[PDB]
Each structure stands twice: as C-alpha cells, then as structure tokens.
Image (tube, rainbow, N blue to C red; front, side, top):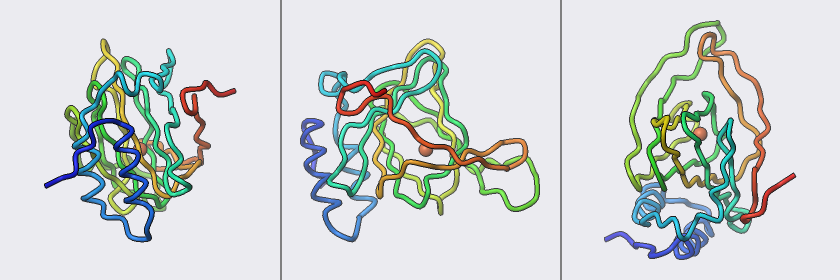
Length: 186
Ligand SMILES: [Fe+2]
C-alpha cells in the first residue's frame, strides 16, 4: 500500500516528486519516510558527531523545496525547546531512540512551560510536527549509545526560537550546519 524506498537514494528521489507540487500530503510523506529501512552503510558518510552537542548534517536541498539533513545525537545529547518557523517538519529515527516532549506555546506572561505529550520514537519511526502542533524538545534517551535521525523541513529555514522552560521567554537562534554533503563546514 505504501511505496517502499529500498535505499536512501530512492527516498530522496521520491521526496523530490512529492514536494514538486504545491500540495504536500503529510501522511503520505510520513509513511514513505517510515517505510525506508535505515541502513547505516548508506548514511554513515553524513554521521559526523561532536563531543558536546548534537550536529546537523545537510544531505539534500530538495531543489529549494526542502532541506533533508541527518542529526547526530551523542550520548545524553538533547535539544532546547524550540519552534519550526512555520514549516513542515518530519523526523525519522535512523539509529538509537529519541524522546520527544511536546510543549504548549507560552503566552505573554511568565510561567513554567506545560508539557502536552511525551513519547519515545521507535526504530525507523517517522514523527511530524509544525508550529500549530506545538513546540518540542527532543533528546537521546541513552547515555551510553548515540542516536541518529533523518529530518525534513519544508520550506527550509535557518533560524528558529529557543524557549526557556522556566518562563516561556524565547530567543532567536541561527541554525548552523556541521557538514554539508558529507563535507565538514567552517
Ligand atoms: Fe525540532
């Protein structure tokens, strides 16, 4: 029932077709990303880790329609609470496991932020978020093993906001790439 890519290259090809138009079937993209069976022989060239924080590694620019990247989570690495600046955001597990915590948006007043959902993403699972869904934080569940995830953002974006869990106040953050196309960045 679901088109199953046999390789990461197949998946990218399919994604080029699915984002060529103006409409994006979210459930269709999600099912097809999920159907790809993570194969580290195919993506190890992108899996470039850092000791202290997670890294973002650009895989494909999707003809301007999306960014496809691989995120490498060291032992214990996690993100801040953040938004996704009005884009579609798909995240699929390639190795290990991430805990996703969804947060409600803050309003004007200062307040501890409210959790709306908490889950662990299973092997090969693809999750979806946008700003209407909520904010989230994601974290490697393991302090002894890495996690690796495949992210697709459409349209692409280079800035987002990080949120202080104690108050709801936010800061603009510029996103940076650790590598592009398997090549380390300055
Ligand atoms: Fe995110």
